[PDB]
Image 1 (cartoon, rainbow, N blue to C red):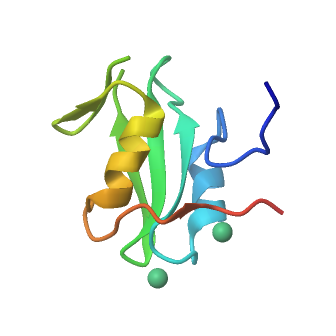
Image 2 (cartoon, helix red, strand yellow):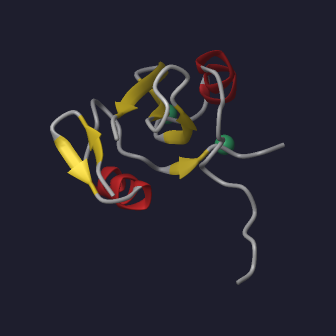
Length: 96
Ligand SMILES: [Cl-]
Ligand SMILES: [Cl-]
């Protein structure tokens, strides 16, 4: 009913732009961007291991590795609770 402030979703953001935003952020700081190469898919970018990880989300059916979810919020919630490689999702990257 009411529009929300922009948060974790950045639409069609390049990998380079995602890195610019996330490099140096505390581990678990993240965003989601549209796939640059595969219409319909997404990428979860997250500060991790002192660098930036980019997890491919393949598409009510969203798959990351061997884990499937029925929505992006569900996927993000799952990885707030469960580790990816070395981090969980903590919070969306802040906007200037
Ligand atoms: Cl950290
Ligand atoms: Cl931030």
